[PDB]
Image 1 (cartoon, rainbow, N blue to C red):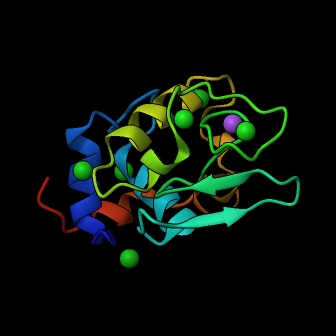
Image 2: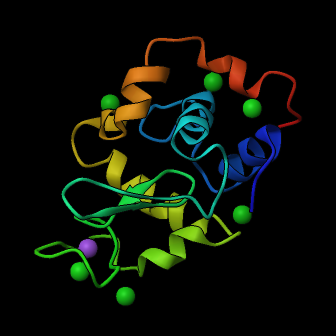
Length: 129
Ligand SMILES: [Cl-]
Ligand SMILES: [Cl-]
Ligand SMILES: [Cl-]
Ligand SMILES: [Cl-]
Ligand SMILES: [Cl-]
Ligand SMILES: [Cl-]
Ligand code: NA
């Protein structure tokens, strides 16, 4: 599923991401924009052989199982395919665990490089929330 901007903001809010660990909703929408362009089916292979999955590009080295990432973990206890669903529940729940892991949203290098410090409220401007 390719979400619309405000559609994704509303789903994220409904699943409890607005101000989760202190990160306003615009941070999450901005991260999803540059990680996946709001596409739940986005996948990208990393140089180390792990793969990133879904709207927030969650990686198989730590967080999900895809059967092909040696030496990896599955800390969210989910098959990585769950992260590609049109239902964002698995991606949200796993993102909550990641953002609690110590480095906040810096875990998402696209968030650090393209969202952090910017006017992220713009990402939810105009939306009925
Ligand atoms: Cl957009
Ligand atoms: Cl915001
Ligand atoms: Cl694996
Ligand atoms: Cl699995
Ligand atoms: Cl959803
Ligand atoms: Cl933080
Ligand atoms: Na894994």
